Length: 54
DNA sequence: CAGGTAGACGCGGACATCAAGCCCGCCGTGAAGGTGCAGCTTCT
Image (cartoon, rainbow, N blue to C red):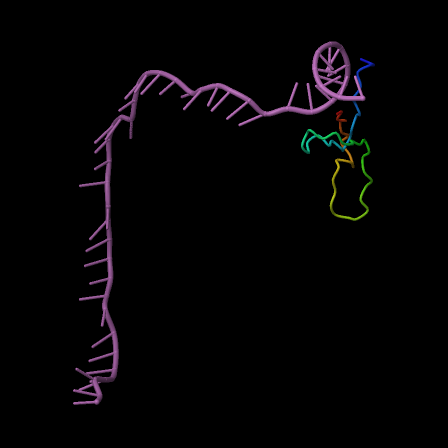
């Protein structure tokens, strides 16, 4: 199991929905809060979220 | 080559009730997955 690798424990970056045969980069970095009033995303100002793993 | 002016077209009252609306059987399947390693193969 320690020999078996592949995990990354993502938060907001899964390259695999975009044409799954694609060996790209996946990130675990939730973005900064937008300073502009109005729009919002990323599920980031409350109600803590689970972490994907690819 | 022409063909009218005027004025007005009613009120009332009512428009049904009864009873029931089926049963049977079934509903396609085939193809739409990636990653990692062991071993083979081909070439030098």
